[PDB]
Image (cartoon, rainbow, N blue to C red; front, side, top):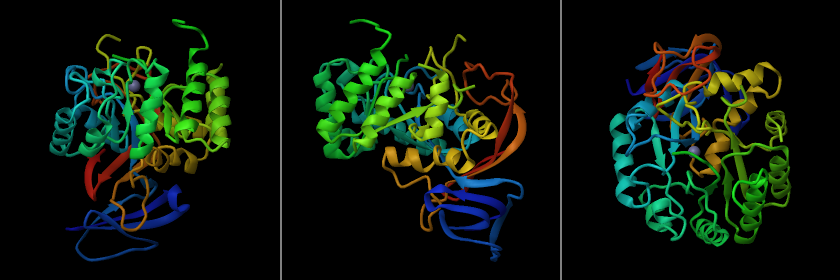
Length: 375
Ligand SMILES: [Zn+2]
């Protein structure tokens, strides 16, 4: 039983431009073969008839509240949410307490993650010691310990020279800087556009990759677009749960390919990111709504959960290439269900989709060839 066949499914791997009725053979935690009609001895068989089989989703924006606020959420609860929403890899932000600005906390997160055993949690480092804004953190030790990106998420880097130093370091190391999330002059209405343009200008001058974690306006999207054409390494994301100057422009942004990836900004709160919502477990049905309304294809939808986020944080995931690890998500685009006390795996409930009928549900999740979630 070292061997798994996913039979009868419809496979989509945008990374390989692969779409069709194929089977998948998994040997030794890894994709061994994709082909029609696979049958081998000593193999578990999953019948994926009527299902869609794709790479495991990757969320590059999750607040796991661990260490510190583990009553809102913790590495285990988030891990469980993640795999139930189709995610085999998640990237946690560093506004923990203590913040992730030293390798002791990096290590705590990696060790906890290995023990829960469900999805692969990749930590991020703070840009500044303390997330305080003044003193730039040790990106070399933090990346070495396992951090895949840096961000001050929950108090964005105001000082424009701090941001410039961060992107220079980032470019040496080969990792993204993530800017502009709010969570736990002054507030101009166009602060966002000015910030994105600043990050663009410093990105071009430094060679550094900047990832915008929140865009709200058409002008913002046009600015991001302008710098992509100019060859600058800038990316951005959007929360599929949030799409239910304009919300209308974001949809246009997803249509036109300006927005690189989906990311939940999963943001557990215990009263009810404004102040932000949980997302992991509903990301897919939300994003399928756009697909049912003809705004994106399924290929594009899956692109934006798999290969595209993978390329931003530079890991070799989000594919079903032969040899890659067998992170596989298997979902039914047409299964109706309800997020409520019966189904919720978060310690928090803070989402406007609570109680709503959702359409699209993950049936299996597989990490490294093992079943880590089953409906
Ligand atoms: Zn955030």
